[PDB]
Amino acid sequence: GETTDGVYRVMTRRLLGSTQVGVGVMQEGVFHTMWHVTKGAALRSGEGRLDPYWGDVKQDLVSYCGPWKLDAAWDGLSEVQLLAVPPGERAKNIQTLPGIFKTKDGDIGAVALDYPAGTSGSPILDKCGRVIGLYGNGVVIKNGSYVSAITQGKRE
Amino acid sequence: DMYIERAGDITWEKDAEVTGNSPRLDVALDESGDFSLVE
Ligand SMILES: COCC(=O)Nc1cccc(NC(C)=O)c1
Ligand SMILES: COCC(=O)Nc1cccc(NC(C)=O)c1
Image (cartoon, rainbow over all chains, first blue to last red; front, side, top):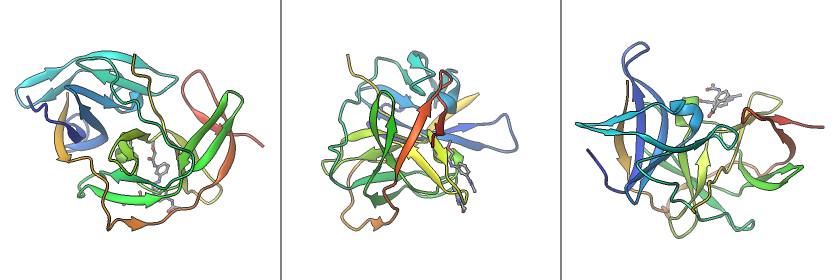
């Protein structure tokens, strides 16, 4: 199939037409997405097949063809870019300064940008183009706006 | 059956639209991976 590094759409043919359920990141031959996008199911890339390799529902992450490769982290100070890939729309970079999710187990960066559910899995980048996490697991605030955690896995 | 299609290179863009605030929110994360607002 297609194994080049980059951002990819995740599609299904089970609902009306072809529906974009999410997005992911190919890096070093491994596909990275949010667990809620695929529920751990196998994927197709042209004539090839990607099988799940690692996943965790609490972290809301899954990798295919190999272990999780993304290890960069938000510095806690600088602006980042969401490389949003919305359903039926061109990939678009949105720059923002993350907020914070404060939890009983530590603080995590959070991005306050309103994109549709099928954008889940889009990568968040630092100034060197490294992926610091995926957008698409968070909370809906008071008026209906959305705030996503910057969700990152662990590279063993 | 799910499938993937390439949508771009992962690069930082100098002319990106800049927007969004930076809220500080107290949250809880449950065993099912759902976040919820705590107050
Ligand atoms: C075309 O997609 C547009 C979209 O998904 N918007 C969107 C996404 C998330 C939240 C909100 N909220 C309010 C109050 O507008 C809007
Ligand atoms: C799982 O992520 C969900 C998400 O990314 N956005 C999201 C979440 C909640 C509401 C809306 N709204 C509209 C109008 O689409 C969008």
